[PDB]
Structure formats: C-alpha cells, structure tokens
Image (cartoon, rainbow, N blue to C red; front, side, top):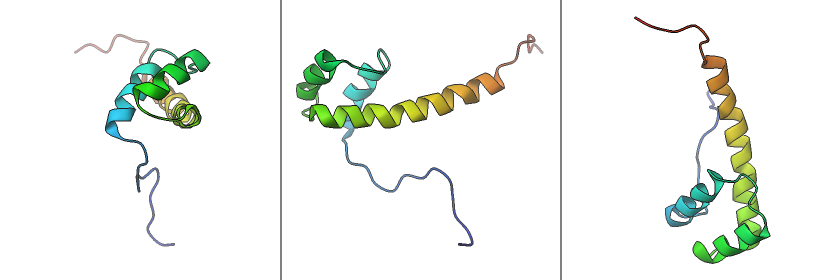
Length: 80
C-alpha cells in the first residue's frame, strides 16, 4: 500500500449503553471474576463470554497507554 494508518476504528459491536457499564467495572477490576462477569451480564444484557473479550482487548489498550504516561512523566518539577 501507499498511504495507510495505525489504530483506526472501522466498526463497533457493543453499545455505548453496554460500554459505560463495562468501563465502570474495568476501572475497578481488570479481571472481573465469575461473580462480576455474571452480575454484569444482566447489567448490560451481554453473554459472560462477551465480557471476557471486551475486557481482554482493554488490557492491551491500558497496558499500552499506561506506558505512554510513564515515558512522559517528568521527575523534575516542571515549573514556569
């Protein structure tokens, strides 16, 4: 190819209504046990299997990002 790109959104499966709940559970625990995936399954009307995935891909988006912040962190007091 000639002109491409990196990390682009083409289509989405889940819904904002389901994501909002999936993000709230992730911000607390990156690995929601069966007691979490099950309870949430009915909270967003999703299969205990789906949650596992959504959370899986997330880890890759968190581990990759979290770093970007560490590489930017500035020990010295950036004042002025």
